[PDB]
Image: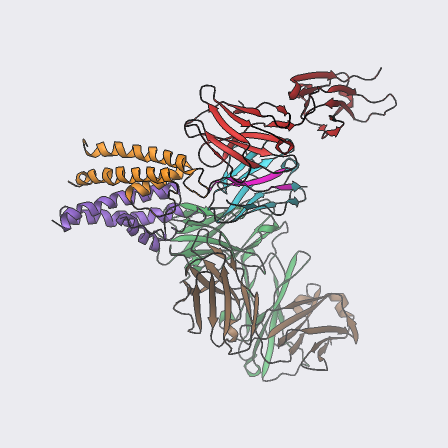
Chain colours: A orange, B red, C brown, D green, E cyan, F purple
């Protein structure tokens, strides 16, 4: 888990940090639906796993930025845990 | 305990500005947002804006002319709303409310009545209302207190420091010559009065005054 | 929740004619609509599922179509047995909801009522009660009037009427009229008569009987 | 065989509660849901709630006041609906139905007629209806049976234990003085009666009674 | 921004009778609707959250239903203390908005 | 297939188990469309492969949980079968 549990730690952070900067960046932009922590966390899980249904997504510049930060740190968190959870 | 404490009233001359406060207690989270809502007499609730104390960012209703500027002091757990260049259109009750970042206003403050007028503040005169000597009493008796010549609104009237709530009617104030007047009614069993004391407590936030008037039978 | 609107509430068709029931959803529900038939005093029965899928056991006569917000249940060549209430039901979103229902009415040829009058039974008389029953059976249209006469004089008190719904056997209607009297009241009268007045005839159809 | 078995009727005094049952047979899957639907006389179908026996969870229609509580017994393959504190508004036919988790009600129970009233149960009196001696018979003859003084609804009337269905009309019951009354009509070829017997069978679920009355020509 | 329509503005009911307040959203907002009660001279008080969730401290008499664009706040057997103004509020999209309110009259 | 067929076994379980806890968690939440086994299984395949069209998705807390369980056990089932079906 020096690689496995290691990624999880980083990930569950971004998730939380993401959901937060998400509602933070999103409120204010009329129409944004990414404006409440609870779901904002569901969005992040979607995003980080790349499933993205579209039920919720970012609509502001920095919003999109966090988003990009979540996707990236997630598409790899899951990556390292991949050559592990299966190795 | 009261989660959100707001001052009772603020008198502001047209064109001037005022800073409203909202002191919060109870659990506080980094995800809390403090909202402000405006309500004119006889009308509905209008959202003004919100602020997240943990970060300090504020958002405002785009549909209305921006009169407010929101700030927050973390150390004193107090949120502030600076209203500037006010007109009579700005006269209303301004509530602060707390949202745990999950969409609903879990709790509201009591609200601050803001009056925009050039008139001066004036504490109310409290007079007793006891039955005349020829009034026939039933199994119940009605007493009251007259509160006149005060400005601006509001005044809070309670009976026996609040211990007496049932049988109480406080009538809406009427405005005449830059001064308000209202009366409050209380009904208790005829046998209990005057044996058991009946006193009305009148608080006038704007003048920082609160007076008591014991109601005793006429001479 | 999804509102299902079924209009018109009543549909009148002639025998052997094709009929179409309408069901409109307040929002798009794909093809997640199902149709049920409910005859008088019967339980609902599935006719079509997922807007147009056939159910084994249901006559080929029944078919469904539509998707989105507008659906149709069709019957090719309606017959008496199709007389019933029809309901749509959606399963696209929770909770499942039902439409308010449409009744199928068949306009057949006029038919005069078959009138039968029955004297109270001896078993009933033994209990101190006497009911005179009259049946006005299998007539159409359903508009009809019944009149009672005791010893030639019109009677109104003690009379209770009941009308059936259109019959899924022959598209006709029927009515019962019951005159209840005490054994005593019944014993002091000779003839009892029931008269039926129906569109099919300018003259009433009368049936009588004497207590003796 | 009958997939869902429900009792015919239940009389409940206002304010009391009742527990309806639905015994299921045939194939049973972990994905089956048992639904309950309410239908007032002359009105449409109203969804009440559902339960998944394999897990025991139940969901209810949010649009209506909750009168029901659903449970299920796996060993006896029986689902139950407890209706509590009923009023006349609760009087109706309550159906149970089975859904294979794919959205449609594959099969329905016969339904339980629930009547909320203070009146007492009363079995019906069944009287014969044979033509008078002066009645002229055609190629067909009409007979019947009078069912009166019963409560509450319903009663099921069949002819010759059900073997005789064609030519049968059962009229809706009429309510008078806390008691119902109805008649059923049957028409057979004039030649077959009385040579071939004609009997009506009257079942009254509420009183757990079922009686037969042979229809013979008058003395 | 989402418009919340509350009609009728006044609802008259007899004592002990069930009453239903209506709230219609200009667009679908899922179940992101909340109801508040405001008595004369009082501050708003949360009654129901997310269309149908109960709030501790509120009489069982109060219930909510609906999803999408149409919502309902119901009171089983109204009593004097229920006399007040009722407001709906949405949190599906920014900014949060309030309905115009319905007064309950007995 | 000690790694390949091995993952498939685990996966076709979650799929089934998922679809089930899905309709189970979803019904009750007014508006949820993830309320019938058949499709609920299609949703799971979408989800587990990360395609997620959005035609169907979870809307309840535990609903989302199952979802997270399906994505995870799927994003790896497909992972191990990856360094296999191509190795």
Residue segment shown in magenta: E83-103
Check if residue E96 falls in the magenta segment.
yes
For the point 34% across and 46% down, the residue is F21
Nearer to the camera, C162 or C183: C162
Q: Is residue B190 left or right of residue A58?
A: right
Residue E40, relative to residue F26: is it above or below?
above
Q: Quadrant of residue C187?
A: bottom right
Q: Is residue B23 left or right of residue D73?
A: right
Give coordinates of residue C192: x percent, y percent: 74, 74
Residue E34, relative to residue D77: is it above or below?
above
Q: How many marks?
A: 0
For residue B196, say whether it is visible: no
Give coordinates of residue C171: x percent, y percent: 56, 75
For residue D160, say whether it is visible: yes
Q: Quadrant of residue A10?
A: top left
Q: Residue lying furthest right in this view? A: B134
Give coordinates of residue C2: x percent, y percent: 49, 54
Residue D76, relative to residue C157: is it above or below?
above
Q: Residue lying furthest top in this view? A: B219
Nearer to the camera, B44 or E63: B44
For the point 54% across and 26% down, the residue is B82
């Amino acid at each position: 888990w020096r690689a496995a549990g290691a990624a999880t730690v980083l990930l569950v952070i971004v998730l939380l940090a993401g959901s937060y900067l998400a509602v933070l960046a999103e409120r204010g932009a009329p129409g944004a639906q990414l404006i409440t922590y609870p779901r904002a966390l569901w969005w992040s899980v979607e995003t980080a796993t790349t499933v993205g249904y579209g039920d919720l997504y970012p609509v502001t510049l920095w919003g999109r930025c966090v988003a990009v930060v979540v996707m990236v740190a997630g598409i790899t968190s899951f990556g390292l845990v991949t050559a592990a959870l299966a190795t | 305990q009261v989660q959100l404490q707001q001052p009772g009233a603020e008198l502001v001359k047209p064109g001037a500005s005022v800073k409203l406060s909202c002191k919060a207690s109870g659990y506080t989270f980094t995800s809390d947002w403090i909202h402000w809502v405006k309500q004119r007499p006889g009308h509905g609730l209008e959202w003004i804006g919100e602020i997240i104390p943990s970060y300090g960012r504020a958002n405002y209703n785009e549909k209305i002319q921006k009169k407010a500027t929101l700030t927050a002091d973390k150390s004193s757990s107090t949120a502030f709303m600076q209203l500037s260049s006010l007109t009579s259109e700005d006269s209303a009750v301004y509530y602060c409310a707390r949202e745990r970042g999950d969409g609903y206003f879990a709790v509201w403050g009591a609200g601050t009545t803001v009056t925009v007028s050039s008139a001066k503040t004036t504490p109310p005169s409290v007079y007793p209302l006891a039955p005349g000597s020829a009034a026939q009493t039933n199994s119940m008796v009605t007493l009251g207190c007259l509160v006149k010549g005060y400005f601006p609104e509001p005044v809070t009237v309670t009976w026996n420091s609040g211990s007496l709530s049932s049988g109480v009617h406080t009538f809406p104030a009427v405005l005449q010559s830059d001064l308000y007047t209202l009366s409050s009614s209380v009904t208790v069993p005829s046998s209990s009065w005057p044996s058991e004391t009946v006193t009305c407590n009148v608080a006038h936030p704007a003048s920082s005054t609160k007076v008591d008037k014991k109601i005793v039978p006429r001479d | 929740d999804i509102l299902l609107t079924q209009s018109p509430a009543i549909l009148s068709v002639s025998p052997g004619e094709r009929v179409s029931f309408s069901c409109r959803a307040s929002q798009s529900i794909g093809t997640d609509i199902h149709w049920y038939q409910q005859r008088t005093n019967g339980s609902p029965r599935l006719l079509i599922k997922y807007a147009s899928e056939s159910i084994s056991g249901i006559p080929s006569r029944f078919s469904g179509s539509g998707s989105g917000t507008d659906f149709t249940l069709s019957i090719n060549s309606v017959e008496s047995e199709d007389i019933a209430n029809y309901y749509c039901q959606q399963s696209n979103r929770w909770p499942f909801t039902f439409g308010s229902g449409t009744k199928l009415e068949i306009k057949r040829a006029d038919a005069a009522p078959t009138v039968s009058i029955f004297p109270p039974s001896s078993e009933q008389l033994t209990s101190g009660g006497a009911s005179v029953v009259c049946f006005l059976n299998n007539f159409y249209p359903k508009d009809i009037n019944v009149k009672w006469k005791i010893d030639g004089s019109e009677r109104q008190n003690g009379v209770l009427n009941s009308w059936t719904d259109q019959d899924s056997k022959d598209s006709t209607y029927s009515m019962s009229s019951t005159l209840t009297l005490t054994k005593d009241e019944y014993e002091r009268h000779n003839s009892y008569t029931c008269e039926a007045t129906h569109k099919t005839s300018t003259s009433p159809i009368v049936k009588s009987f004497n207590r003796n």
